[PDB]
Image (cartoon, rainbow, N blue to C red; front, side, top):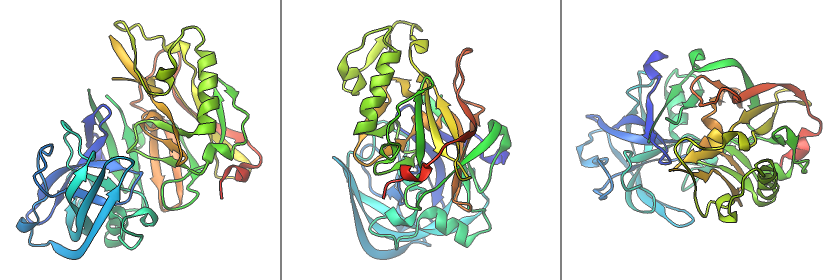
Length: 370
């Protein structure tokens, strides 16, 4: 699918977006690819931060649903008017579908000043769509209305400008090396998965794996960091702090309350441990592990970086920190997510991200939270 290669762009920390068109004639917009939500929402008014916006008055195929939607966040939020219209992805499958579209008429802390995107494409399932699971997510409409396979894959390459590929309806084997390894999608709402073991430099935290997924563990392209439950994060950092004991860093650093800087290319990468997450495999008692480097959780912001690992109350969230090291296949058809070493991931000549298996892991089910 050469046509779809390199169809993602963005700026460090501002997420990855793909070009899309909405309405008739087609109105072009850059839309954030978010596997962590399920609403297709686009700016529809002249907010100062927006390069452009959806103008419903110019679309002959626009249809009003006469319903509003308010989506609150920890601080900001977005609110819009629901409708449907014809949507297409220029550098994606050659098709056009009628999908729900929330026209954003008011928001706070949603749009980013200086960013180049005007909307968000929630690729998750209806269960978490707003206002409720009755609002059919875009991908569902795309598959239901066309012959596009129920699957998509993401290769986030993270470089201030970033790039990547979203292969819609398939897999592009040139984007990865080695074999793809699959972990089951526990439940179809967020792209939930189960982490069965966690290793730092090869030594595991030996913590009731159930904690690792309290109350969730998800794969989300819309989040920059690797979010971990408090308990897991506490021990996580504890081990990383011990591995990197070579140098001393402030407590704020580990809490993302302050940045850490190093002179021109003087970052002590080797001082930091690799993080290995073992994921539930496809077979009983079988697992595999994906391993990332500081290159992923120690990202640039001298050279100042922010610890890309943080705590959560919503569970584990495998964001760009994890994804930028692998080619990730969202195999909706088979309810599984595949990981393979990405052909574009950044690595030093000493350590490289990897996906290895099979491994024997017992009681993987006790890792899932109910």
